[PDB]
Length: 282
Length: 68
Image (cartoon, rainbow over the protein chains, first blue to last red):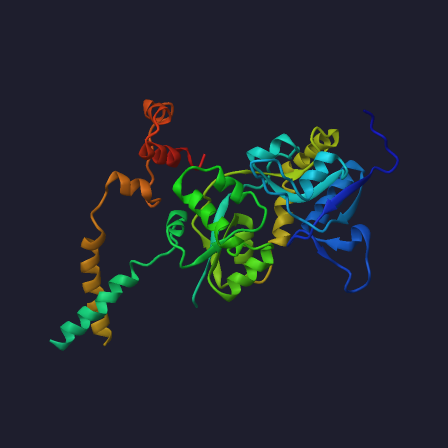
């Protein structure tokens, strides 16, 4: 195999994410790399400066990574990367143990784990005191979520997951009661407790009390962007982070070198804080 | 009424510290994440739990092995 260089134009497939990929064509029409903006495009531009490589942003209908049954099934990014028909897929994807055999990831730079978000709903004297304290005691025995386990053993408050993620794969391979009961609730009701898109979960949370089992940065991002909710507890597990690259790609090593070089100077640290500034709690 | 509310809160607390405490059973400690429990590293307890298949050993071993 050889490396042919004319302009190093790369096939960069991607899908829309917040605050990663979003359009800028409402002030004047823009296309190609100018078609979008966000943290992802900023990373692309910074990497292009370091490597002297050209990238072309192009979209696909699906943003899912495919669900894993007892037989192999992959959708969206993963099949393209296996087939080597798209040079890069810079959509952010966490590292789980099963996806390391078909594609290469980059070394993690931001640490993460599953976490949950919570919507908020914002003689005579002796007898009256006894009656009042009778349910004052009851109201202090209610806490449907104070942990993942507590969320597991009740269903009066609805919870779900984003379609085709890593969470359901994690639950189905976990043999302890909490995760398998989460998965059993997810499969039941013909996926009506699941949302095909994150924004569907956003409307579910805004309308009623809806819980999502997903990565933390999304949770504290919604917290920083809405003051009617906050992150519950801490990280329940730890799993890696990376950028999708072809399996065995020589360009992956150079990309990792460049992102590490950006890592020592702490430029990504300030850069994410640029996108970590917005309107939430005053 | 406010004094009645204070008296009711005190009475509810008096009921509840005996409603809920003191309990420290091993199953209770295992089933809650409020209290952390573990042991030394590379000890005999983990080998015993891994070699065994009792559900209790499995759940405590999962708890320690959790959080990396």
